[PDB]
Length: 4
Length: 71
Image (cartoon, rainbow over all chains, first blue to last red; front, side):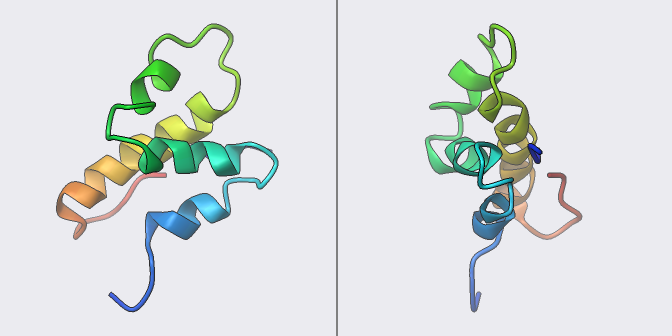
């Protein structure tokens, strides 16, 4: 879900 | 009821790309992009992964938002  | 839910859940998806992406997931039709992005992926650009867990989750709750919630 998160991108980093 | 006094604010949004998955909306900001996406507002946090790294503003870099995962942000507007996850939005895409729970923003367009439940399958407008959730698919073209979480289905015919070539090398997993970014919105598909981010927005795949964010779109799928949006569904899980949005349908009957009441129990736990995924991404």
